[PDB]
Image (cartoon, rainbow over all chains, first blue to last red):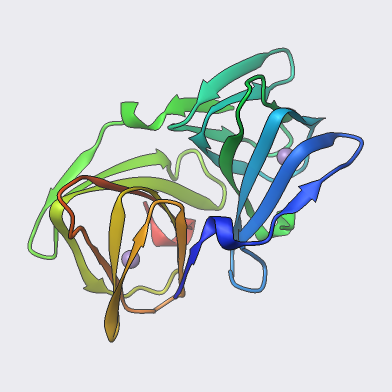
Length: 114
Length: 114
Ligand SMILES: [Mn+2]
Ligand SMILES: [Mn+2]
């Protein structure tokens, strides 16, 4: 049994073509878990995970702040206490339109990576 | 994409010998999920999920309050922002030793039910 403070995990700041202003923490990863993985994402004010898709699902829980969710033909801003399920191959992305950091847990099957 | 307020999902109170002072909400259940499910548990002050084991893992994230984790040979109390991975067949239980409600997300592979 691993019991850990999520904040104590070293984050990877993520800077790509599609991602900026985002830190990722892998809480429970591929070496720990037989089936799925748990990450914690922090998005800085104005941070972006642009639209993309992949052949595996996301189960997400919004932990802090107002999270803007990008969809194929629209967006929806939700907040802390919402859960989100993205089906395999469904176009999605995220953005922080607020002036404070937003946090969300994101879980994916091990096929998806980590 | 499902986007919903967790608190809007119908809670199942449980009042039995081994599991009491608990409310369970299935956020992403077996009709929605190809691989694993997402539940939210609220534990009232003094509530209890007694020690047990089963042949599937738990991945857990503590959302609010101070949660006491019962282990084979001990106990460890963690706070919101902590995560817990319980290995398959590992003895585990939970208790709320505080005077306020505790909330945690709990996910298991679909093999484990709901
Ligand atoms: Mn994605
Ligand atoms: Mn259990």
